Image (tube, rainbow over all chains, first blue to last red; front, side, top):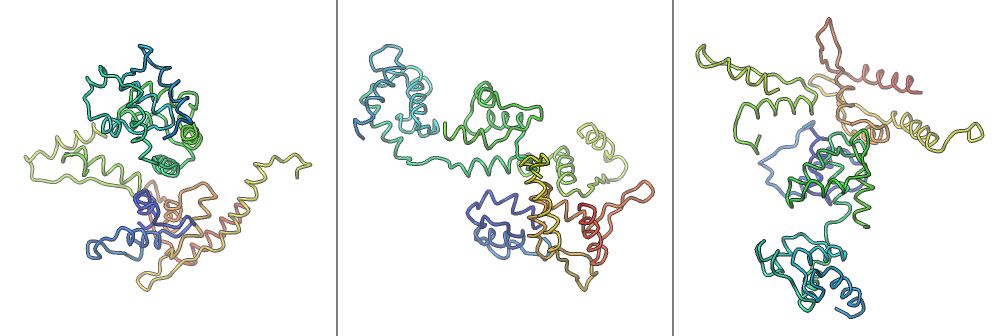
Length: 48
Length: 148
Length: 49
Length: 97
């Protein structure tokens, strides 16, 4: 789910997210972009 | 570096000498280094200790002459783990984010992870801060350890 | 699971932790023809949990 | 209220729960042509709410969008829609106030 991913893996890319309270969707987007992983190995769902 | 603080350095070095001349065991001199604010992991200590073995560490001491380049190499770290690291990692280490962290889990994951320490080490570390909930406020203890 | 080698204890652990985290009730279904040992695994999981 | 004998910490907690019930309005739900069940597009408002409320966000929005009802003796998990979820959160605001 959106929220669990970031809270579980913000510790990995700590500098990724802004310190403000941002929704899990965009936070996950930005953190995964900051991971620089291939687009095919994963997918963004509308809820997961 | 400078003789500015080398006086305190000398008195501390000779303070913990078992022979009283300027020869202090490798474990002991690392402990003094850590007591001097400069507290690195024993890994880089052995790395700059000529990569000795435990026997050499407990048999071979060090003069004050080589102690200066030794703290010089220690000062080449120029930084250690940050405070935000510790607070966020302990916050995400708890099970429910209840402003605190359980005690027994902390003791276990401290004596049984990465650098190994004895049980009484982390015991007197957490000692005094215990509570009936078993969930200690990680913030106060981590800032006490950082500032202290 | 990825840490430990494969075992049914790891299966039960994963099921329980998933139920705890996602709050979704987990379930376990053992299958196989009679004589393949559908029984021992179940009671072992029982004592494990 | 200070003359009444109200400590500062309970005053701040009162102000924070009033903050919570104020923020409760900004919760928005989205309908989908599939089933039109309640969906949270951007829970940052609910995020801040449950944050200053002292409850997890995930289980909270799960319970809201999915109510753990109980029929007979077995629990059932249905799906919520715009009307029932909005009514539920508004009744929650009423009860909290």
